[PDB]
Length: 284
Image (spheres, rainbow, N blue to C red):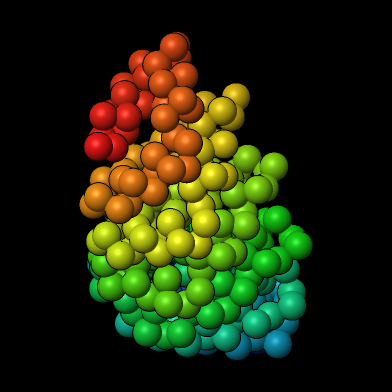
């Protein structure tokens, strides 16, 4: 676009009129969706403060589009995620989790999910800003797109270190996640299994928490899914749980995993057939 495109957009973020504001937001989103180097160009131009400022907008539309812009920036490398955090976006994003506006909620979850796709300490900034209780509550949303986006944010957080895992457990996520294992929405099963498997990649007592929330029978049932991608996430999760100690192993046996796993030997998908064998030996 023109060589002077970026400074002009950044200056329009301080425009009195909504029409000019929205054009700058659409354009900055478009630039920031073209890879890390273009995101950094946007950051170096000074966009973050006016974007954060706009999270306090009275206007539904701008807030939504500002969130989307910020979301795109946070999809960059760790350095770029940290710049979003350093610009003070978190306290406002966390407040926006109590919003009853669905598009706003969806774009705030997206941004926080991206931030949580970072290093362990940007995961921890999200936790320290108080995001978890609200996030967990949204696993109960009737609106499956809010729900999908909350699960993806929790999953990213659960993919951190063991204290990240622990914080997810202490925020009360296990019962709502185990519940979502009954979901016939495949993207929700996929995200909930992935989140459970991340939590199950922790210590033994973290695995035991997953066991005690009653995950195993639904997990074993999902070994019969005709959807290969759900089959794949369930195996991976069950795989992580079987990687614990003796009583974690013992619980998976008790849950009937064995003929589900044997029955997966006859599978066409060699990745599936191998992993299946691996969890089979991997108990006892």
